[PDB]
Amino acid sequence: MTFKLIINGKTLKGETTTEAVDAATAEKVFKQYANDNGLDGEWTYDDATKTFTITE
């Protein structure tokens, strides 16, 4: 499936998608991005809209 995580922070900013088997993996894929970049805040999950977000 295809997901869409909106990047929101100081170090990182913008938007992008992620192809994972499930929402759980979809986050693990981007986890390296926000981590390697240092950007970290609060992970939001919603089944109604099926979208991921992060605020720093």
Image (spheres, helix red, strand yellow):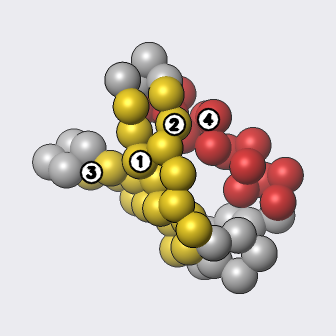
The residue under label 1 is which amino acid type?
A: Lys
Q: Which residue is mark 3?
A: 46
User: Which is more N-terminal, label 3 or label 2?
Assistant: 2
Q: Which residue is mark 1?
A: 4
Label 1 element class: strand
User: Which is more N-terminal, label 2 or label 1?
Assistant: 1
The residue under label 2 is which amino acid type?
A: Thr
Q: What residue lies at 44% left-to-right and 17% top-to-bottom?
A: 21
In three-dimensional space, the C-alpha distance between marks 1 and 2, rounded to whole angstroms, equals: 6 Å
Q: What residue lies at 40% left-to-right and 39% top-to-bottom?
A: 3
- Residue 42 visible in the picture: no
Classify 10 Å Cα crowding around label 2: few (below 14), some (14-19), many (20 and above): some
Label 3 element class: strand
The reply to whether discs 1 and 4 touch (Cβ–Cβ < 8 Å) is no
Mark 1 or mark 4, whichever is nearer to me: 1
- Residue 46 visible in the picture: yes
